[PDB]
Amino acid sequence: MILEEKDASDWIYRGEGGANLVLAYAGSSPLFVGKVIRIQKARRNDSVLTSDEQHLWRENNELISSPNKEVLEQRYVQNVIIPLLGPKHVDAGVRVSVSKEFLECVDKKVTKQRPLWRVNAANVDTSHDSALILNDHSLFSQGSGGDCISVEIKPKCGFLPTSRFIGKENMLKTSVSRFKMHQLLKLEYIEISEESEYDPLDLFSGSKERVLEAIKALYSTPQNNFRVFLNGSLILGGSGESTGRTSPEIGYAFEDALKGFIQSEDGHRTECFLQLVSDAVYGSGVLDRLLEIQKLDKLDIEGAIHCYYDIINQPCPICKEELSLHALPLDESLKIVKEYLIAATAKDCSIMISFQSRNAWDSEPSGDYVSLKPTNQTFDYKVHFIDLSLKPLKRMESYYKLDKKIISFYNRKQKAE
Ligand SMILES: O=P(O)(O)O[C@H]1[C@H](OP(=O)(O)O)[C@@H](OP(=O)(O)O)[C@H](OP(=O)(O)O)[C@@H](OP(=O)(O)O)[C@H]1OP(=O)(O)O
Ligand SMILES: [Zn+2]
Image 1: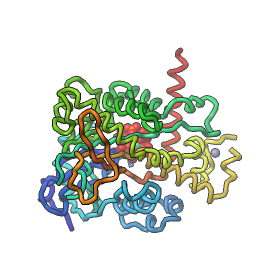
Image 2: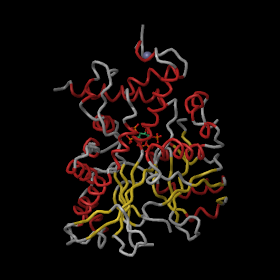
Image 3: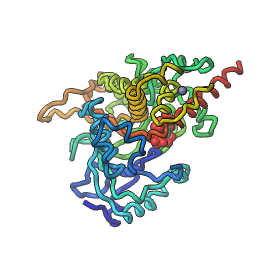
Image 4: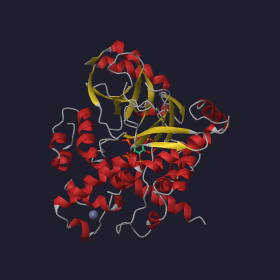
């Protein structure tokens, strides 16, 4: 039930977000085999919910009355996200008690494998008594059936806004994806080495070859959006951070890593693998449902921000000295902001697609599979949504400032024709 210090050596680094560090199990305890632990970080940037947050998530009491942030995250996924996405592809993760010594031991144990800039920003919140055990989807099913290749995509937002509330100078937000605009700021802030080739509009397009174009793009410039695992081990993409362009060195390493799984002449494993991922993505149409959650951002931050200030009962700084939104009932305003924060979740979650050579000996042969015509292989696949985090209400402020920043910088750069 409780993870003590000694257990620390059994977990190895897997990756990290901005708010969570993730370790994969390595020991042999039946409880944790094929599981990962998601540990919340203590940001120096920043009870379980603010006074305003209880007001918003009011319709969902199991949420507002949570003991810790771990159960809060659990109940959010379970009570808000599942009903929207389906329980087939989402698991909320079992909670577990952890000791302060365990956490402190883990933090120091992994410090060396972490990106420096990540360490600068946060460590594990050693005040928490809890943590989350999820399944290790770099392993196919629970408990085996031969090697497993899995891909983790962070697709980000795949639609263009359409809001009335987009200002006059900012109307370029209508044409260009937020992702592409944001790339110019990251590159400006020395957050990435070169602009990524990826355009989420291709991935979400519902078009077969635009999906392939996206997967190819992802492979070329993975940054923080593309990872590939072999039996849990990272074989492509950055570890808890963005990575540089796929060089011929990296490309080759990955090309080697795929031996046997994709059954093709040496050198052609990579392009066939990409085809496979593209086919599963498109076939499953699992993106369509996600994009729907995303499109719950009906009004865009420039619209929704006005509602936020009505929620937190403060004079809206964004209107100086719109009738439309500020005349809405409190009820309607809460809906808008809630759904914005849900969309937010959806825009930052990641997909895991686990592959495995079709096992003819299954008790119930899977519904979902991809036939690889050229290599004569059939692969079974599963899709799962991960990193489904509740976004904190106060963030509404920083969302607006950030967006304003992106769109001004993009306009600024364009004005140099
Ligand atoms: O720290 P990074 O890996 O560069 O990614 C951050 C981070 O996403 P993670 O959840 O993956 O860390 C932010 O979330 P927090 O961890 O700070 O909660 C998220 O912001 P929101 O999820 O609040 O939108 C932001 O995404 P965005 O840039 O869309 O705000 C995103 O940055 P990138 O995904 O652009 O790298
Ligand atoms: Zn306003």
